[PDB]
Length: 216
Ligand SMILES: *C/C=C(C)/C=C/C=C(C)/C=C/C1=C(C)CCCC1(C)C
Ligand SMILES: [Br-]
Ligand SMILES: [Br-]
Ligand SMILES: [K+]
Image: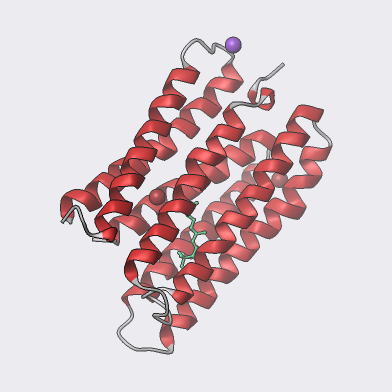
């Protein structure tokens, strides 16, 4: 069983999410700034949730826990960004709403019994994602630019990383088993794991290493 590629990617994901969680916990100890503490809580929770979900897929070894993890973590990552640019509550609610639709229709597309329809759900989900990225890239950038240089600079990096990583999910899904079935399952699992770790641990490393989280 341990020789199967599928199991290996799940095991590596579990290890990387767990290590990232522990490292963020270590980095956060000592920090007393009220503002920085909020970022540490959110950013530490994200890989912790993914670790539990990745561990679950290992114990179950199934990918239902995948969408469950995305359902919880994507809105948290959005909160992280919203907090950095001090976004309005109305805009935050719209983002979370679109995010729920994105993950939700994504699951419906994975569960659909008939072909052709797989892409209908993928299209609706991708539209939801495009709205989110449009808000992050054009909307949030304006607010960040009117903020402290450290904040404007860090937001732009996180934004660029988020846009690229999130955009890769619909591509992988389409070429994977839920879509056209071009790429084998083990490769698709590898791709999603790499994206998950990069979007959570990588994203968190960039954010938490920055002075932009402090109130100052
Ligand atoms: C930690 C995990 C993250 C940041 C996951 C992000 C996932 C997405 C942006 C997923 C998007 C999808 C679509 C746009 C359409 C097809 C189905 C999904 C759910 C794979
Ligand atoms: Br995840
Ligand atoms: Br806003
Ligand atoms: K401090």
